[PDB]
Image 1 (tube, rainbow, N blue to C red):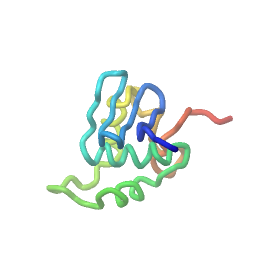
Image 2: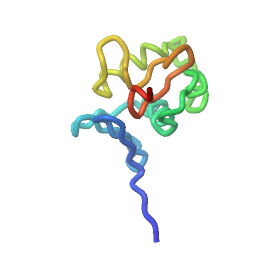
Image 3: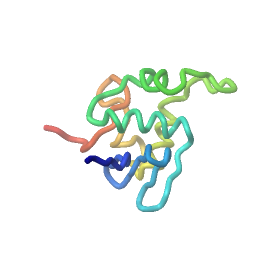
Length: 109
């Protein structure tokens, strides 16, 4: 016998494919379908770095009504939606010069 939750947790954020949404702070963010998809993608790889476009090309690869892939800013909205820092998320942005690493904790050594 086996059973799984399909809920994924990192800090005070919980991402949920069992309900296709997310909670933060026990208080129910509800990300957009793509912001949730890309967040899920990163969080489901979390601790591996994901090169911005690799993520978006996994979920979408679309231009919308001329939004010109404002990826770092859109992450800078995931930032306050995941309880994160004022200038960049400790959870996500760049890591060094690469992508979006969704972290588990922000320091290895």
